[PDB]
Image (spheres, rainbow, N blue to C red):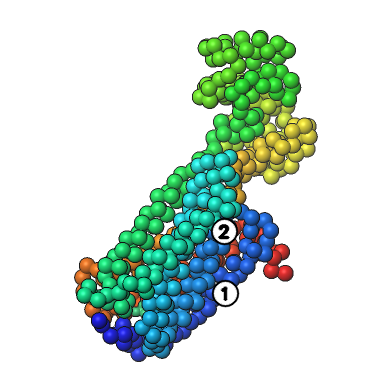
Amino acid sequence: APPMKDYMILSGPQKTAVAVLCTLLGLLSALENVAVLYLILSSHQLRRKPSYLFIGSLALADFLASVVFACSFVNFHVFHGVDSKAVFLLKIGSVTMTFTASVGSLLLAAIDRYLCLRYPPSYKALLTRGRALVLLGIMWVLSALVSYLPLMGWTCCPRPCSELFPLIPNDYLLSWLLFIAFLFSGIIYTYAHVLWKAHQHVASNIFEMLRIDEGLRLKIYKDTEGYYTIGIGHLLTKSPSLNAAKSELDKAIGRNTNGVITKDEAEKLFNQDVDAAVRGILRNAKLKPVYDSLDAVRRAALINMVFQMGETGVAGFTNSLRMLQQKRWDEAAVNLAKSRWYNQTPNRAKRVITTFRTGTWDAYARMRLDVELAKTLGLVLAVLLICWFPVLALMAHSLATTLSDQVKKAFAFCSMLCLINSMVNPVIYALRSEEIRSSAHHCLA
Ligand SMILES: CC(C)(CCCCCC#N)c1cc(O)c2c(c1)OC(C)(C)[C@@H]1CC[C@@H](CO)C[C@@H]21
């Protein structure tokens, strides 16, 4: 077995360099984690949600790691400290558990977001307050099992020992690294899916715009005016007869629908009405110049208006139409707010008016705050990936070839990044998370 002092390498000023960085970063990391752990339990709206149970569990795994790692790293390297032979297997095992639990905490946070975005109405039933804690425990137990194995019956006896960590073999590290790479593969595969489903909800085009405003329905419905309609506002007949509307439906689809149409039929019939709306605007002397100046987003906002009150109606908004052509967005936004169209349908008008001033689909963005929560995580996962890649790579190199004191020195400075990662992560939540930033004004006082 190799000696304990052989793993202590400090070429003069690098001993006081770890002493100034590791002690400052480790105390500052435990300062932010405690400001997050209490914050989740302090606010009534944050404690109930399962997403914040994984944010809290990360801060819990980070707080304990920030104190256990910074204590034992400065102790062993800077002050040449050796507590006991059994206590060391406890120190290392405690660091191994707290940092593995940070990874696992984020995997559950990534799984939480996958279910939320992939299956949104079935999320609240697929993931409950209890189920999240059951998943937390399972993750914490498997964290402790893989982390304390050396402490238990695993140690390097006839098998070669690791040149980075004392008393631990190459075979156990290989096992933990492969286990951690399995947790990372889980994170990468689950989050790649999270970004794909988040793009689906932020995706906008006119069909998805008017789907919100007009209201999609594959069954025959009645519009505000009282006439029979189908899909995205496709008025069938003004007539009070449903059988007349049912006949009009079979006429417009070319099949015996019996009151129900398919989604791609509603999309077919929609683009049929959009093409017809566009032609109407073009064959309108007052509307065409306005349409000519508007972009792919603002053009859709005008078609939205033509869908609502027809070409002859929209053409009447001469005051606003002049501003839309002159690109005076803010002046048109306030002028349109002074219309009867805003006084009759404020809900829809505000959104339409916004698309005219911003030039963005943000006004029609579904699940925006739940989607921005997935964005927060992405950055947290990026930092995690950045900081941990050099540390794990040196541990992988350790098992394949023999490494000299020059590599051993470099590993100690990479180990400092885990501490930086755990310090940076609660700052990301303190800046992006809107629910945390909104609670930051009330909870602290
Ligand atoms: C943060 C981490 C990268 C976690 C790796 C988990 C172990 C893998 C398994 N299974 C890590 C890196 C370290 O360099 C060390 C760590 C933990 O723990 C203490 C107790 C502070 C050690 C003190 C003695 C040093 C000997 O050179 C190694 C120090």
Q: Nearer the viewer, residue 304 or 288?
A: 304
Considering only order in the chain, which callout, 2 or 1, is on the residue closer to the N terminus?
A: 1
- Label 1: which secondary element: helix
Residue 408 appears anywhere in the view: yes
Q: Position of residue 234 (x, y in %)?
A: 62, 21
Q: Identify the disc placed on residue 428.
A: none
Of residues 304 and 264, the one drawn nearer to the viewer in this rendering: 264
Q: Is residue 76 above or below residue 121?
A: below
**Residue 93: x and y, percent?**
40, 73
Question: Which picture quadrant has residue 83?
Answer: bottom left
- The kind of residue on which mark 2 rests is Leu
Residue occupying image coordinates x 62% and y 12%? 246
Whether residue 40 is situated above or below residue 17 in the rendered picture: above
Q: Residue at x 64, y 24 (%)?
A: 233
Q: Residue at x 46, y 44 (%)?
A: 196
Residue 359 image-quadrant placement: top right
Q: Could you tell whether 98 is left or right of 277 in the image? A: left
Residue 396 x %, y %: 28, 66
Residue 414, can we see it?
Answer: no
In space, the residues marked 1 and 2 are separated at their CA atoms by 19 Å
Where disc 2 sits, the SS reads helix
Q: Which residue is mark 1?
A: 31
Q: Quadrant of ligand 1?
A: bottom left
Tag 1: amino acid:
Leu
- Marks 1 and 2: which is nearer the front? 2
Q: Position of residue 148 (x, y in %)?
A: 39, 70
Camera-side residue of 160 and 6: 160
In this figure, which residue is indicated by the disc labeled 2? Answer: 53
